[PDB]
Image: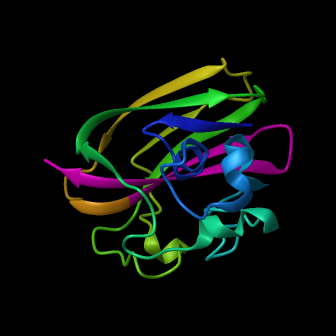
Amino acid sequence: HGYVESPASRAYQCKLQLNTQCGSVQYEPQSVEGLKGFPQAGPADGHIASADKSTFFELDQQTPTRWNKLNLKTGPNSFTWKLTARHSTTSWRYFITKPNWDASQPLTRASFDLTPFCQFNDGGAIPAAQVTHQCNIPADRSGSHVILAVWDIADTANAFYQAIDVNLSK
């Protein structure tokens, strides 16, 4: 259980009241939990941002202006998770939408480049309460994009999914 605090994820921005019409997740941003194994298995297409959890359905809405986007530069960026439960961890992966994705369609595997721009494999270790990853956001992305941070749990069937809405510039 945890969420990306910086750059603030869609779920966390819902808690901060920066996003609108978020429903349940604004009261529990740390619990966007679904099945692991993405992209071969995992949440179904169109249900990735909610991790296919019924009460988190609002997160699966997607339009060009639907979500509040953080202005970031491409290149070196830090991603920090705040964990409320430090579960034994298989991996942390950060994916970004394709260069020419469509923000007016639901998030599906076709929306994302399925080669993460960075990945950290922890071998089942128990993480600290705050975990920070430093990676380069691909420089060939500009404007509105979604970064999907995925945390796969080693000792359960689950993973946590954190969509992050961003507006990139050089």
Q: How many marks?
A: 0
Residue at 74 percent of width and 21 percent of height: 126
Where residue 37 sits: x, y (%)? 71, 57
Where residue 69 sits: x, y (%)? 37, 54
Residue at 78 percent of width and 38 percent of height: 154
| Residue 165 in which image quadrant | bottom left
Where residue 109 sits: x, y (%)? 53, 72
Q: Main secondary structure of the magenta part?
A: strand
Out of 74 and 10, give the one closest to the viewer.
Answer: 10
Residue lying farthest to the left in this orientation: 170
Would residue 147 be counted in the magenta stretch? yes
Q: Does residue 122 show up?
A: no
Residue at 57 percent of width and 31 percent of height: 81
Residue lying farthest to the right in this orientation: 156
Quarter holding the N terminus?
top right
Say left or right for 11 vs 1: left
Out of 68 and 4, give the one closest to the viewer.
Answer: 68
Vertical placement of residue 26 versus 105, above or below: above
| Residue 90 in which image quadrant | top right
Say left or right for 169 vs 111: left
Q: Does residue 52 show up?
A: yes
Residue lying farthest to the bottom in this orientation: 105
Vertical placement of residue 153 versus 80, above or below: below
How is the structure coloured here?
Answer: rainbow
Would residue 13 be counted in the magenta stretch? no
Say left or right for 169 vs 132: left
Say left or right for 170 vs 100: left
Where residue 47 sits: x, y (%)? 66, 71
Q: Magenta span covers which residues?
A: 146-170
